[PDB]
Image (tube, grey):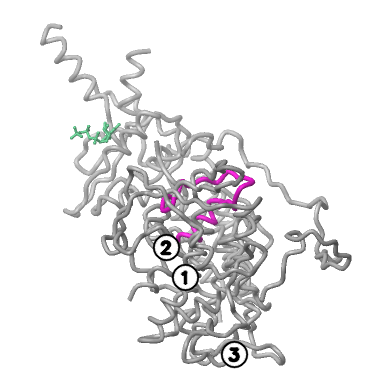
Amino acid sequence: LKKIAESFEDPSSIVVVLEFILFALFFPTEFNRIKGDIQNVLLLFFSRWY
Amino acid sequence: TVTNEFASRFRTIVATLANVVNERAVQDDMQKATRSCTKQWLRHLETQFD
Amino acid sequence: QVGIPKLEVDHISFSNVVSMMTANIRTGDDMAVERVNPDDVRAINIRNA
Amino acid sequence: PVEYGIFVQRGATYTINAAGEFEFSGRNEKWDQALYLSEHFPALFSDVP
Amino acid sequence: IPADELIDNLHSWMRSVHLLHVRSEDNTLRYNWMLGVYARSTNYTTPVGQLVVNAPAILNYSNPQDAFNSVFVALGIDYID
Amino acid sequence: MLQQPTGGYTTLEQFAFTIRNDGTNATPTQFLQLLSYEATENELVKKTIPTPETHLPSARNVPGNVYIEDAITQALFGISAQNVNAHGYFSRLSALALPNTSARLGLDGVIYNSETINIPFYDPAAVANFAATYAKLGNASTPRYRADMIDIYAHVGLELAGTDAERAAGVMPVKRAKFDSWEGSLISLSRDVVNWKILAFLIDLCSLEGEALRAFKTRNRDVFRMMLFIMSTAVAANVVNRKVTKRVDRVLEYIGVNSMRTAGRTATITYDLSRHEFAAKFLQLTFTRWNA
Ligand SMILES: Nc1nc2c(ncn2[C@@H]2O[C@H](COP(=O)(O)OP(=O)(O)OP(=O)(O)O)[C@@H](O)[C@H]2O)c(=O)[nH]1
């Protein structure tokens, strides 16, 4: 993954989450390759939001 | 003839993300604003996708 | 038997096995990085342990 | 300042539960007009002594 | 100090405090009073504080150790002073 | 493949363990005779060593042939080793843990992913018994599996300094080791030990059973004790020399007490925190195998 630094303080940070979802829809394969590296970002998103 | 399963799926996704954003507690007033705007932007994303 | 260390005895030795690095290993080179600044200064957490 | 500290320790906002009681936020925060369509109210206007 | 004044003052003060929390139906929970008080004392500026603010429900716990583990893992911190 | 003898692999001359001493290749046992002790008022009481975790860390998909013996010995004995858990190659032992794996542990101490020509290697069954325990070096640093790095040293002292009576008792006075010494003795002892083919020792320790294992444990007790001595000097709070009428007596205080020091010193090898975590884990596993 081309790494994203994102704290997820602002609600707008949801954009990044959507950026992944779209990528997982448009490109399930390439996503499946980069997806753990995506999980590293998502874990920040969850620890902050949930 | 009318329904596009892809677009409908993105509708449920954006609906979920919107209720996720809606439920997001925020401290600053500006965050409260971005929280309300993000939902509109989500709605826009949904139409663009459809 | 293990070999006697060359530094243990007083004899001089003129064939030795010097380890060295090939062109593949490199050290002391400058290193490129992508720094990414915090999105908002007011959101930075100075505090928690 | 002191009346303000008491007031704002009760909280800047409130909601009205199904019982009709005002539950104050207990939390200092600025209002935004977003909240105008929310369940929240500015607390200054509660008229609750 | 006259008792009436100590009482009126302590009463007004106690009424002034309002710990953040989520109410819940489950019988097994305890509010994590220490962390909620500490988040209040720092006006929820510390990362534990803003944690308490966005997720007040994190103070509820059934197992006493997880009351702190959930906070340490949400925060990535090794400790809290 | 080198078949393991009825005794250990250590019975073979190919794996003699010897420290250079007085101009000769002394056996470790005859070095330990030089060792002498001064009891202090303080006491070591050996506690039960906690049972090692069942979890073998997953070997990562590593294309290369890891030099495992070198990593282990340098972590326990190396003068300059540091950050031994950052690279994290000890997990690789777990590759050998599987029944019918293509991996081989060469006598070189390398972990080939496939059997390869003109490289002698240990019998895969014995290596499997070995790896089934020692792969757990691969989680020496992961917090859930970290070994106690304080209490375990008591056992070190007991197996090193301990008289047979003190060992039966399970408690001994905290002693202070000493021996007549040449210049840079402890460094040279540590380098003579880092060159040891200790995989033979550990493989035999894990693979042997019954009378063979017991005979191994007696025949090789002083080897183990030498490793314990290098390790202990790495954790000794201080290491002085004493004049003694035109002779110098090296003195390390104290045996069986990890001072947790990480500052380097000329006298002996030093454990960084990671080296401590590793040695602690190693001693946990090895002492577990040593008693059965
Ligand atoms: N701020 C704050 N400190 C606490 C809280 N709970 C416990 N402590 C502190 O934690 C420390 C450790 O507990 P102890 O000192 O062993 O217990 P103690 O309160 O002195 O009670 P005893 O030991 O039985 O006399 C104490 O110094 C307490 O003051 C809390 O909810 N808020």
Above or below residue F250? Residue F218 is: below
Of all chains, the one bearing label 1 is F
The circle drawn on residue A7 is none
Q: Is residue C18 left or right of residue D37?
A: right
Q: Which residues are magenta?
A: F255-280
Estimate the x, y position of residue A31 in percent, counting from the top left. Answer: 62, 71
| Residue type, label 1 | Lys
C-alpha gap between disc 3 and disc 2: 28 Å
Q: Amino acid at mark 3?
A: Ser
Tell me which residue sits at (60%, 60%) in the image.
Answer: F189
From the top left corner, tell me how far across and down residue F180 is, in percent: 56, 52
Q: Is residue E15 left or right of residue F38?
A: left
Label 3 vs 2, first from the N-terminus = 3
Give the alpha-carbon distance from disc 1 to disc 2, as whole Å: 9 Å
Crowd band around label 1 with a 10 angstrom C-alpha radius: few (<14), some (14–19), many (20+): many
Residue F59 vs residue C40, the one in the foreground: F59
Q: Which residue is mark 3?
A: F102
Task: Bin the neighbour count of mark 2 within 10 Å (Cα to Cα): few under 14, some 14-19, many 20 and up.
Answer: some
- Ligand 1 within 8 Å of disc 1? The answer is no
Q: Which residue is disc 1 drawn over?
A: F136
CA distance separating discs 3 and 1: 20 Å
Task: Determine the image quadrant of residue F275.
Answer: bottom right
Q: Are marks 3 and 2 in contact (CB under 8 Å)?
A: no
Query: In the rendered image, which quarter contains the C terminus of chain F?
Result: bottom left
Please name the predominant secondary structure of the magenta segment in the image.
loop
Q: Position of residue E53 (x, y in %)?
A: 39, 40
Q: Which residue is mark 2?
A: F145
Badge 1 and badge 2 in a common chain: yes
Pointers 3 and 1 within a single chain? yes
Identify the secondary structure beneath mark 1: helix
Q: Is residue F229 visible?
A: yes
